[PDB]
Image: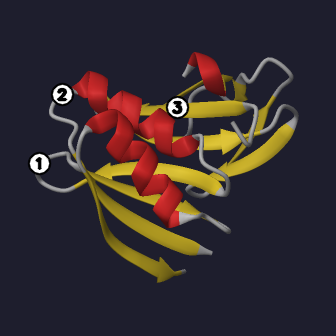
Amino acid sequence: RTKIVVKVHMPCGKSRAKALALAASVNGVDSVEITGEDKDRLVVVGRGIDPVRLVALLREKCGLAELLMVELV
Amino acid sequence: AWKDCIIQRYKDGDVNNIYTANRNEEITIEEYKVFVNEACHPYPVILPDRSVLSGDFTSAY
């Protein structure tokens, strides 16, 4: 049970929706959340998530994706 | 697409939460149990916190 936090470039609601769906596609993701005062962080929660593959996918499709944190939960 | 369905959750003017589920799976969303049928549709649709559940196959987003 890991929780992964990702800064993603998603300036409008259409990109927040694309990023949410894109993270969800990745093996082990149970939930994805939008957080931060600037609506620019994904909190990805699941089991067995490959966080390098997760950030690479969001980076490829959103331009910017920074892995801020991985944590057990 | 490691799971068939994406359940979207609309509360307070935005979808800020989405959950995965296979068809005919029961997931938990916060304290609530949600059943997701063979068409990726979630039951109940309105959670007790008045948030609104929506679903479809993953590729349709």
**Which corner quadrant of the image does residue A67 belong to?**
bottom left
Residue drawn 54% across and 80% down?
A73
Q: Nearer the viewer, residue A35 or A19?
A: A19
Residue drawn 19% across and 45% down?
A39
Within-10-Å neighbours for mark 3: few <14, some 14–19, many 20+:
many
Furthest-bottom residue in this view:
A72
Numbered circle sitting on residue A12: 2
User: Could you give the CA–CA distance between mark 3 and mark 1, rounded to whole angstroms?
Assistant: 21 Å
The reply to whether discs 1 and 2 touch (Cβ–Cβ < 8 Å) is: no
Residue drawn 84% across and 41% down?
B25
Horizontal and vertical percent position of residue B12: 29, 34
- Horizontal arrangement in the rendering, residue A8 relative to residue A58 (left or right): left
Q: Earlier in the sequence, mark 1 or mark 2?
A: 2
Q: Which is in the foreground here, disc 3 or disc 1?
A: 1
User: On the image, numbered disc 1 is attached to which residue?
Assistant: A38
User: On the image, numbered disc 3 is attached to which residue?
Assistant: B8
